[PDB]
Length: 203
Length: 241
Ligand SMILES: [Cl-]
Ligand SMILES: [Cl-]
Ligand SMILES: [Cl-]
Ligand SMILES: [Cl-]
Image (tube, rainbow over all chains, first blue to last red; front, side, top):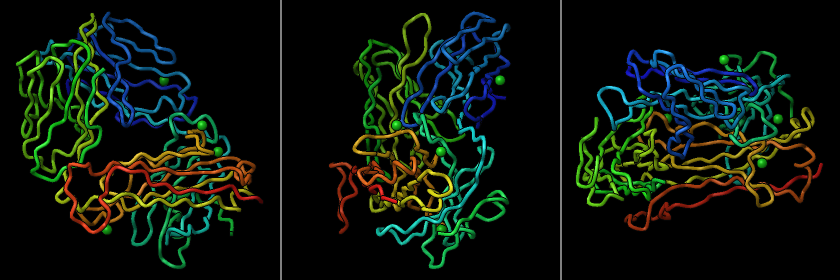
């Protein structure tokens, strides 16, 4: 057990879901701090909780300090793409007035809510500037995962994450590509990866 | 505000370098962290005040100085591959609540040879007529390939304005040659608009990859262009049905 245990380490949620993430210790803290960190940025302080048992609200975010001052939770109502990021809890533990210890964080991914999944693989037209044939897997449910792979000539991407600032056309996709002649979109996006009822329209 | 420079940096193993950190506020306490996958934020060095410096938890290969209150530089005398990391300078707030204010990070990549550094090639792939027919939506695919290190920012531009709506980007680049130690990287992104918007040949679509490369101080002796910090773009125009 670490001085500060954050759970869960990774969280993938859909737009409009509520969520709670936890910061737990066997040590009593005089105060706990929450930071948010975005890619290409330093952590930014959100709030500090100081009074045992207290709640602090920062818009859609609610922070609770446990009564025994060994715990803190961060609750988000109606998750938005803008909520995506790393949530760190920190405190002066292990004999420190000046040195903060940072928990490992919850890395929050906010995925689109897809009411009517319509999973499909589209063969794209070649680019004049590349020798690659590209296949677009799109319109799948946010509970469907695609993990990156290289299997000989065939590359598949991890499924993409919404631009944090996206306010429309929020959908799931992964791509596959190969430079081999006669590349088949069905080769890359096979039954181990995609839903069985995935649609394969001809060009 | 904590100011860190540079934001991105490439060095060969063994060539001394300094990352600067200065704070406008008058704070006594400043510190350096590195952030690595699975290892959280690890304290390298801290300075309680002017001319006071103390090794953190992971000091080996680093030095600091605190001649002035305003500046707390991080010195790598002999950079090694293992010092490839994201570095954060922190200063301690003096209010009732002693939180930290952080710089915007320095992404340092330490390389065996500068000849391993390559800018991206960038291609755009136009929306499928099959997608347009099935969905009345149109997805453009941007593919950035052949870049090293993995120091890129991909953006989408429609009619000369950056867009965010309809943008979905791979959360990290993939290695093109993962069996090899010096693999270059690929990264994809999608921009989705209505079929109507795509079908308007006045509409212009550009995928931009900002690559963070070599600086002026870096020596270059290869035939191919010095891979300096640059944008590489690919474009498409709307296509009438
Ligand atoms: Cl909840
Ligand atoms: Cl959409
Ligand atoms: Cl937008
Ligand atoms: Cl390989």
